[PDB]
Image 1 (spheres, rainbow, N blue to C red):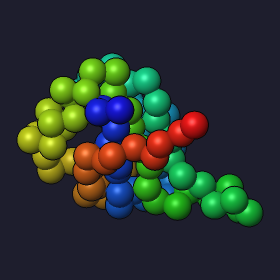
Image 2 (cartoon, helix red, strand yellow):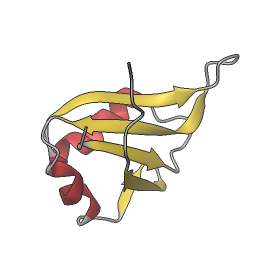
Image 3 (cartoon, one colour):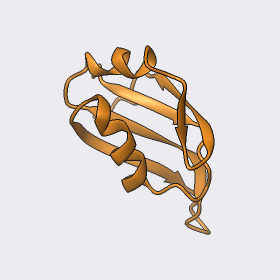
Image 4 (spheres, rainbow, N blue to C red):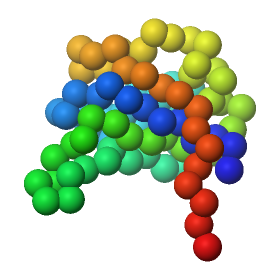
Length: 84
């Protein structure tokens, strides 16, 4: 997979729906999650966005800085977790 972005530095208030809304300005999104604490269900302050078109990752990176919910957030390209 080529189109996955890690996004760090999120406020714990930011929902994955809001995260997706923000990053859709750079392309169609096929997955967007905010990682949650297993016990509490609260955001851990980071997530992942997967673009349908992997060329959109570089478009995000060259059009910063990025702010969401009053935080400067930290999008980075990532090599995705591999499955079976």
